[PDB]
Structures are given as structure tokens and as C-alpha cells.
Image 1 (cartoon, protein in one colour):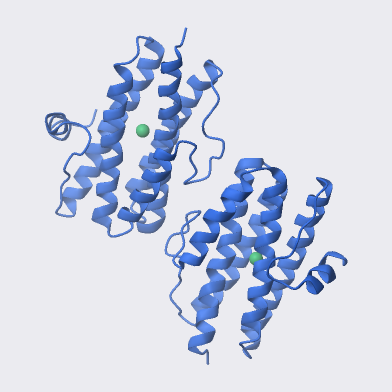
Image 2 (image 1 turned 60 degrees about the horizontal axis):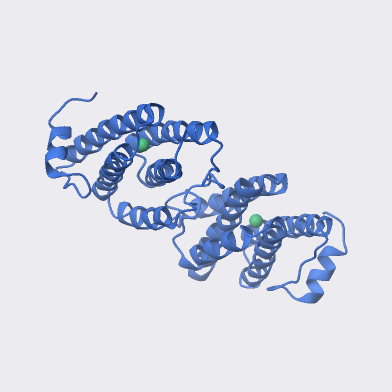
Length: 169
Length: 169
Ligand SMILES: [Mg+2]
Ligand SMILES: [Mg+2]
């Protein structure tokens, strides 16, 4: 059976995946780079994966309003506002914001994975983590096309270099 | 030819119609009352009408990002945040917010109509105004179904009572 603390992590990840979908839809609509629309769709899949686990355990869904930008945990509301404002400044800053959210996602997924032995909760967290590694590689390669790069913020420098120096999984 | 001041009014109305669409899509997604989805669609039509005039005169569109909640004029950003928070409290408060935005829209359309002799700009402002009267009647009748009513904020009491005491146009 699921612990109260394990429930808290699914409730955070539910909205954390929604932060990524909503910022990437918002930055698609500003810059019309296909990467944001494609990765947004992947984040909608990740949101649906967390929702399936919330419904499995009948945990109340923190997403009471699917609209872009709406969050129950104000951590994610603050991140949405900060990151859409930064991403609005240029294509390069929007792509950096892409990488930033995946970086956060990987760091937070490692924290929650280390708090659980439930193999079903772990399959999903590991899958989401692999997705965020792939997405990070895609945002960083597109940053390189614009003559830029990315400095990790939440994961370690060692882990970031392991991700970017390896191929899409 | 269009004046600088007439251009300013189309630029404000472009986003004012977007405020109504975006708040009503946000409140649809919270409460799932069909009125919000139906009227949102009408507001998308009103946004497109203003856009046609902006493109006729090659005026830069203040909507650089169609995403819900994004605005160039921070008047509309502040109104969006205030009104989605109020509308989140109950169905009655969401329906009051419906009426509030139409009320504002009618008051602002009267201000801009009185600033112009361009008959093309006026056909559109009058049509939009008629739409907002109709929408107001619909939100107030739905408020009545919930045992509530609406107090006008921007238009006069006399004008509000003329609108609600008459039939859909
Ligand atoms: Mg994700
Ligand atoms: Mg309208």
C-alpha cells in the first residue's frame, strides 16, 4: 500500500509535468519552434501517466483546472510565471527555459525515486526521467544550433555532462 | 485614414476580447458549465474581427502570444489574474465574473465608439457591443438560475437595467 509521503510525491509530479507542458505550449505560441509543440505533447503524455497512478490510488488530483498556467501548488505557479517571462526574451532564452524545466524534473524525480520502493511508482518515475533526459538533449542540441549552450541548475554538473555526451535513448 | 488614437483603441480592444475568451476558457475548464465554452467561442470570433481591422491598417498586433493569460497591455494581465481567482471560488462567482467582463466590454466600447467617425471601425464596435449585451443577458439569466443576480460595475445602472429587461438580440 501507498504511503502518505508517496502520495505527496505523485501529487507534486502531476503538476510538475503540467508545468513543463504549459510553459512549452506558451513558448510554442510565442516562437513557433516545433520543438516546443512536440515536447509539450510528450509532457501531456507524462501528465496522463501520473494521473493514471493518482486514479489507481484514488488520490485527489491537484489539477482541478487544466488551463495553461493554473496550478494548485504555488511552487508551480511561480515557476510558470518566472519561466514564461524569461523565455519571452529570445529563442535562445526559450530554449534555455526548455532545458531548465527538464533539469528540474530530473532532480525532483531522483528525490522522489529515492523515497519509494513501490515498483509501479518507480517504472513511471524512471520512464519520466528518461523522457526528461531525452528532452534535455533535444533542447541543448537546438541551443547549440543557435550558438549557445546550457549550464545545469538542479542536477549535478557530472550528471548533466553524462546526459549531453550520450545519445538519445 | 485612421488616426493614431483610433489605432490605440483597436489595439486595446484586440486584447480586451482576448481577456474575455481567456477568462471564459479558464472558467470552463474549472466548472464545466457549457455557457463558458460557448461564449468563449463567440469571444474568439470577436478577437478575429478586431484582428481583421488591425491587418487592414497594418497595425502591429498586441497579441504576440495567443496562449491563455498572456497579454501585452498589463491592464489585461491584471484583470485576467484577478478575475480567474474570483471565478475560482464558486459557480456563482464564475458567472458574476462572466457578467463583469461583458460589463467592462460594453463601457469600453462606448468610450471608443465616441472617439471615432470611421464607419468600418464603428460597425465592428457596435456588433461587438451587441454581442456583449447578449452575453451579459445570458450570464445574468444563468446567475438567476443559481438564485443570484448581478450588480453593474462599469456601465450605468440605467443601461444595465435596459439590457437585462430586454430580450436576446
Ligand atoms: Mg516530463
Ligand atoms: Mg466580446
